[PDB]
Length: 257
Ligand SMILES: COc1cc2c[n+](Cc3cc(OC)c(OC)c(OC)c3)ccc2cc1OS(N)(=O)=O
Ligand SMILES: [Zn+2]
Image (cartoon, rainbow, N blue to C red; front, top):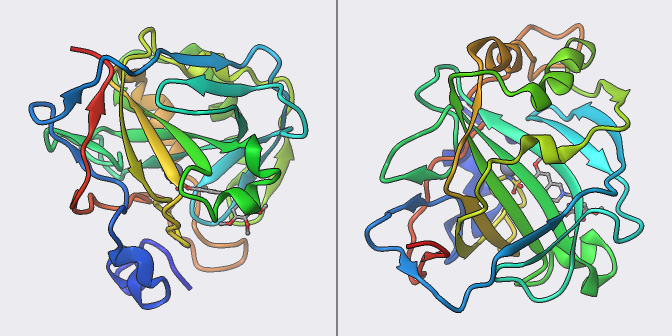
């Protein structure tokens, strides 16, 4: 089954998921000199004041915080989107070294990690239906660089000890995702896919220009999670990122000049 190792990593995924070689795969390198300023793009509207986090889970390839998406509590709208998208979860991708870990790159520059906030289009009623649609999901991507600590991330960092191995989960209530956002909401956008299997091409990507800073002590605690389940040979959860895919017939648009 798929993963990020030598024998089951991204270069192998196409054998189980032929769409891995598709026309709108993610992530991509963002070439800042060929991205196109689009003045018709609206500002992002991020309404997270009513968010209700539920649980944090090690799913064997990442860790994720899940939210209550049974109502329009935490929604994303505006930008390139039509309609309302509800926040479902966030998770991270990170590296074994501070020079790698992000999935998207900017002028070939890799960041230490990348935060994905996954939202689904309420027009489709449930996330399972949305993944079958070209505009089903919107993923907000935020880069992490190593520097000063990010205080709003520390509650996540402090609980990772309790979900060290695959399948462990814990109650994780009253977490405010607004503490993870950069100051500016300037963004690039392009049509893309999930970066994990089944790699469905259902995502409007929104990648923020401004990275957030995290401390070396914060990101080191990511690197001590395990891919394996408890009682299996230990395997540190690092480099759980898919490399950049061909842009093919797509245009990256920028909201900022
Ligand atoms: C942890 O990484 C991810 C978890 C995801 C989890 N989901 C949830 C999901 C995905 C589904 O199908 C793919 C579902 O229908 C089978 C479904 O029914 C409830 C729920 C969707 C997209 C995801 C994308 C993810 O990665 S990414 N990098 O493309 O944002
Ligand atoms: Zn992701």
